[PDB]
Amino acid sequence: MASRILLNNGAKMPILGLGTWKSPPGQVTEAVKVAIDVGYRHIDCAHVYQNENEVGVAIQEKLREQVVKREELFIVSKLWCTYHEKGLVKGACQKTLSDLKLDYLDLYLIHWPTGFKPGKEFFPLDESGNVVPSDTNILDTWAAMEELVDEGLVKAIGISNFNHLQVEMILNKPGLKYKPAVNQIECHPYLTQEKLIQYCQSKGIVVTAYSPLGSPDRPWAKPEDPSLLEDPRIKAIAAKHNKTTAQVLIRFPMQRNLVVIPKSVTPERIAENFKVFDFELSSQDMTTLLSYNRNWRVCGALSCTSHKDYPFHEEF
Ligand SMILES: NC(=O)c1ccc[n+]([C@@H]2O[C@H](COP(=O)([O-])OP(=O)(O)OC[C@H]3O[C@@H](n4cnc5c(N)ncnc54)[C@H](OP(=O)(O)O)[C@@H]3O)[C@@H](O)[C@H]2O)c1
């Protein structure tokens, strides 16, 4: 298992990164510092997470300490839904760059295909509780992302939470200048994503798997929800390999040629989660884990189900 995957912009991306959604601002600086110290070279960020300044403190301190060089890091962020307008994209990117203490991003993603009305609120509501859309179509947002490449602010651009028809719309865009490098989607044994993964891979788009552990700290968790980390069937595979359940859940997407971004703010778990390059799941293990699919989503964007670009009505 090599540590990096080649993107269609010619750059290499580390297949293991550190997630930062829900990482508290008072803990994420140390989390990122520890991650870099124990070998992580890829950090997954977003403006909507409200902690990029604190992530950036860690990155800058490790660059200053010469623990790593900037060229060895792969920093990802995402354009939030209230910035899909062409006149807002550059400023949104530049705010993320300023907060992260960077001159460029390695990868910048459209966070969701759904654009929302600009303003201070990340989920602007009408008086009846619906999210207020933007009129800007995703192809125009894509053109604005392409401009960021041509201005030197980002090395690669991509998408997140796009269904296969939405990926295809980007690939079929009149005058397309840069293909998406990555589609970042939820993926784990309860949401295995065979169809969308094969489509993206067949087009040279690398897939990143988010919520690989089933996001046990998601805000809307209910006790009756299925739990990957507690599933006896997955625990049994881990025991057979003398690894933790989390380590199996991280290795699983790696063996599907995916990038994976487990989140932790716990130093011991950050280190544990990186120790996944020294064992192999068998083909039988892989097929067994795939068999657990139940189309269960951590992130359903449940307030956006009437948005014209809501991604999860389509089968895939
Ligand atoms: N593009 C998108 O729309 C999108 C959506 C969701 C997620 N993401 C990205 O993907 C990342 C990962 O997804 P996620 O944050 O939803 O969840 P996740 O990585 O599946 O799970 C994180 C949870 O697992 C715990 N954990 C981590 N390592 C563990 C271990 N070895 N043993 C036991 N528990 C462990 C963490 O606890 P502690 O932190 O307390 O250790 C935290 O509660 C996000 O942080 C974000 O960067 C992107």
Image (cartoon, helix red, strand yellow):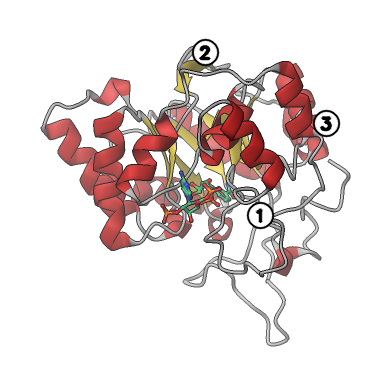
Name the one closer to the observer, 179 or 161: 161
Q: Do the residues labelled 3 and 2 touch (CB within 8 Å)?
A: no
Apparent side of residue 122 relative to residue 63 in the rendered image (left or right): right
Q: Quadrant of the C terminus?
A: top right
Q: Closer to the observer: label 3 or label 1?
A: 1
Whole-angstrom CA distance, mark 2 to mark 1, is 27 Å
Whole-angstrom CA distance, mark 3 to mark 2, is 24 Å
- Residue 159 visible? The answer is yes
Crowd class of label 3 (few under 14; some 14 to 19; many from 20; radius 10 Å): few
Whole-angstrom CA distance, mark 3 to mark 1, is 23 Å
Tell me which residue sits at (57%, 54%) in the image. Answer: 215
Apparent side of residue 198 relative to residue 275 in the rendered image (left or right): right
Instruction: Tell me if residue 181 comes above or below residue 308 in the rendering.
Output: above
Residue that label 3 marks:
195
**Does label 2 point to a residue whose CB lies under 8 Å from ligand 1?**
no
Instruction: Tell me if residue 64 comes above or below residue 141 in the rendering.
Output: above
Give residue 227's mark.
Answer: 1
Q: Which amino acid does label 2 sit on?
A: Met
Name the one closer to the observer, 35 or 114: 35
Residue 269 in the image, given as x and y percentages of width and height: 39, 44
Q: What residue type is labelled 1?
A: Ser
Residue 51, picture quadrant: bottom left
Apparent side of residue 286 relative to residue 212 in the rendered image (left or right): right
Crowd class of label 1 (few under 14; some 14 to 19; many from 20; radius 10 Å): some
Residue that label 2 marks:
1
Instruction: Tell me if residue 110 comes above or below residue 168 in the rendering.
Output: below
Tell me which residue sits at (19%, 39%) in the image. Answer: 60
Q: Helix or strand or loop: what does disc 2 sit on?
A: loop
Q: What residue type is labelled 3?
A: Lys
Q: Helix or strand or loop: what does disc 3 sit on?
A: helix
